[PDB]
Image (tube, rainbow over the protein chains, first blue to last red):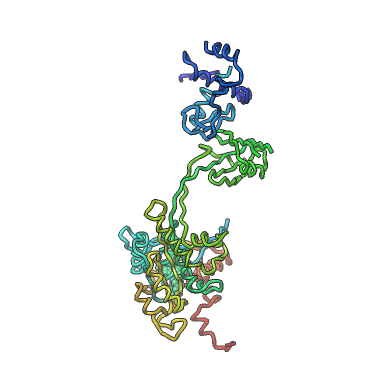
Length: 113
Length: 411
Ligand SMILES: Nc1ncnc2c1ncn2[C@@H]1O[C@H](COP(=O)(O)OP(=O)(O)O)[C@@H](O)[C@H]1O
C-alpha cells in the first residue's frame, strides 16, 4: 500500500499565541502605507524632509480631513462582504467559517515580522 | 416515563381514514365504520383547508355514543397543527366575567388564525471571556468551528454581567431585542455559523391580537382578563388592520375550526348571535354535535329538533350517524385493545361484543381495562371470558343499575 507522506510543518496549539494592540495597529499602518504605495507587492524620505519644517497653521497638518462622523463599518478582509465577526487572535473580521479558515491559513499572524 | 397526555377515550383516533378521493375505509387510522358521516366530514375538512367559503356549520346527529365526538377528534387530528381547532363544550360560554355572547364571539375569534412571516438574525455560542469598564464592555463568543469578539453596548454588557461573568455559559443573542438565554454550562456547544438568519413564522389568532392590542400589558390571554373587549375601537380596527396586512404581502389569514360539543346547552340568545356571527367574512367553519332529539330550547318552552332553533338549523347542514353493528363494535373494541396494552382472546372479544351490544358501546370500552386489571390479579396473561364475567358482575352499567332500584332512596 502507498504510504502517504504527511507534512511536518504543523504548529503546536500550546505554542500558538494571540496578538496584541500595538501589533494590530502596526498591521493597519503597514497595510495603508502599502495601499498608498505603488510598486512590487523615496516618498517616505520626502515626507520626512517635509515634516522637518512643518508647524501649526494653514498647511497639510491642519488641512487633513480627519475622522468622519459615521462610524467605521465592519467590512471583511478576505471577501470584503459585511463581517459581523472578528478574529480572536488578531482581530481581523470575517463573515463565514470558510473566510475564517482562509484567514487563519493565509493572513493570521504570518506577515507580522 | 408517563407524560401529561395519557390513554383516553379518543386516543386511538389518529385522524380520518379517507382515501385520496374522500372515500372512507372499513377500518383505518383508528376509525371504524360510520362511512357516511366520515365521508361527509371529509368534505367539510377539505373545504376548510380551502378556506374560500366563510361561515359554514355542519351538525352531526344520531344515537348517543355513535362516534359523534370521535368524528370531530378525527377531523382535528387530520387537520393537524398550524390550523387552529378550538373544541369547547356547550357550557364553557356560561361565565361570570364575560357574557355568553361575548364568550361565543371570543371562541369564534380564537377559531381564526393569522399567518405572519419574518426574518431575524440569531446568535448561539459559548461565552469565553467578558470585560466591563465602569459604561461599555467586550465579549468573546465561541462555537465548535469559530470564535469572535464583540464590543457590547451598555444594555448588552449589563445583561451579560447579570450572569456568571466567567466562561461556561452558552447564550443566545437575538440582535433585534438582545434577550439572553443561557442554555447551560458548556449542554454541548453549537455547530455551524455563530450568527445565522432564521425564518420565524407565527399563527396568531384574532383573539390574541385583540388581547395584545387592547391594553397596556395587554397579554391577559393567560388568565382570561379580556373582560368585554371594546368592539367600538379594538375589534373593528383590528379587522381593518388585518385586511390591510392582507393583499400587501405582510400576512395571510388561516381560517380555523370550531367544535361546539353538546350544543343543546346553548340558549336562544347564543343561537340568535350565531345567526349573524356565521355571516361575517371572518366567520370560521364549525361543527356541532347533539344527543337529544326533539327537545325544549333552554330559555323558553319551544320544542325544537336538536334543541336548536329552526332559523339556525336552516343555516347549517345535518349528517345522521347509523347505529353500530356487531362487526363495527368488535372492531372498535379490538382497536381500543391495540391502543391499550391489553390483549384478549377471540371468545373474550365475542363475549365483550355481545355485552357492548346488549346495553351500550361505552360500557364494553370501559370494561376492557377492568377485565385486564382483574386478569392481572389472578396472575394470567390474557383477558379471559371468566375475567370479563367477573367484571360484568363487579361493575354495573346504566341499564342494569336503573333496574336494581327496587329499594327507595332520597329524592
Ligand atoms: N366508528 C368508531 N371507531 C372507533 N371508535 C369508536 C367509533 N364510534 C365510537 N367509538 C368509541 O366508542 C365511544 C362512543 O362514545 P361517543 O361516540 O364519544 O359518545 P358521544 O359522542 O355521544 O359523546 C367513544 O369512546 C369512541 O371512542
